[PDB]
Image (cartoon, rainbow, N blue to C red):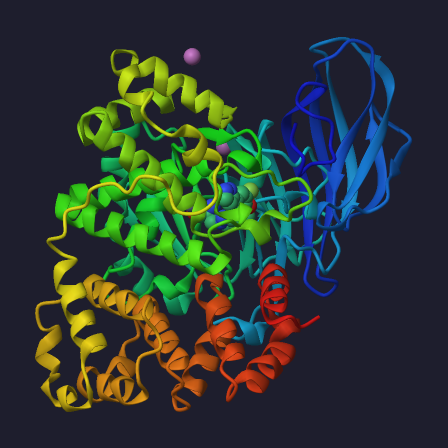
Length: 607
Ligand SMILES: N[C@H](CO)Cn1ccc(-c2ccc(Oc3ncc(-c4ccn[nH]4)cc3F)cc2)n1
Ligand SMILES: [Yb+3]
Ligand SMILES: [Yb+3]
Ligand SMILES: [Zn+2]
């Protein structure tokens, strides 16, 4: 049972295809059109079905050319309102019908962000982008909003002729709108069955540049050149991922660089990965996010979690594949460095929530819980830690990569649960069932806090980060002048970030230490969003007032929740910046992404 959906479960009926014909209205901030759902009955004598909707205005529902009866139930908070549709004829098991729903989105659609020209790079055109994961597809169109149902889709999107529409699908042509010569229709086709949370749309003054045989980088004109260089390893990463998980079945692997308000690092929308512009560091140092979104073309998009309770399967395996891709390109010691850093991020999440918090569990019960609120590093890092621990237990990376490939093949185009994964792991490793029977499955899968067993990690690249971090932490005022810019000479940007992350776990440091760090390291000049973020968190937690405008700026000039959310919390926890953080949130709230606004509001306790 998917307790996050109000629609009929896959055991009643299944959506096989969506044909979406819509028009993007920027003056009304509305998406108007028809969603034609080809639904297949799974039961005999099926006379009605229920769909998910959230803030959708419904004009009518047409089945076999005639308007049919429908009713919208009472709203269930973030879940939206159920939409019951009366079928005009009873269906036998396996019978299909097309249900054509005329709908209109609310300007407040939690799935969309409408941007005025001033909120874009070029300042001449408006912009739109969607974010459907996890349960926001219902805020775009009426659907069975559950990863347990996979469907194909075709789309026709009418937009002003000067703009470009893009979707998580193959571009299937374009023409002037016959009903409106000032608009253009962009056509799309997604031939591989996907869960609806993967349906994506972007409309803006977009340009493209080819960066590989099957990859174009899309963005506003001002960011194309920077993006083309930043993500130039995409094809090499696709070839490694193909070697690890089998053929790439999606045809195209495009990347879209979104405006700074994009709430996530990346979103694995099939054919068109969505990335935050905060990845544009100038040196490819944040390319693991691309390796991660590429990996989802197998774990997540081919093998999908049946419900959001089993989401760890999506991220845990993706982070596992991502670290193998980066391990193949830069070495095994680098995979251990990232894996160890990942354990440190799990330590932080477990500390923030508390070691008894149900959100630190690998498998959660999301009944009555908004998935956006449960979202954190736990499914990622705790999931990864389990696979890395199993890898060491079962004979090493080469043996465990054999399981991952067989796992992807076995469950391709399917939605599965933690028990499905576990039976397959036990089946594949039948000659090692004694080893598998030593795993504390109850604690690993269902217990809060840190995992019962910590894997083994090579320390070659981490040693230098811990050594410099410990030198600063143990330093007294008369040791401050022993620090020099030469302390960072043999540290890569990743090692600088791990140095700051280690130091931040012991924050605050004395204000004079933080002041000396800026004197010798000039961390204020670093543009790399990951390093900048940790440095400003260190400054704010260490109570440096000079860092307040810098932190307020980073929290508002970009909207990637990984940075915006903790920056606002740190600023709210510091008495000197508390009123400023609260006022800044209030004035930016209207211009913010609907989910980032809700979550920043909750963290700050501002309604
Ligand atoms: N996917 C790309 C990465 O490329 C980024 N992205 C965009 C949107 C989301 C998203 C994913 C899941 C989600 O809901 C859930 N969050 C956490 C848990 C959980 C906690 C412990 N165990 N399970 C279970 C959940 F259903 C909310 C938002 N992610
Ligand atoms: Yb075609
Ligand atoms: Yb079994
Ligand atoms: Zn992911």
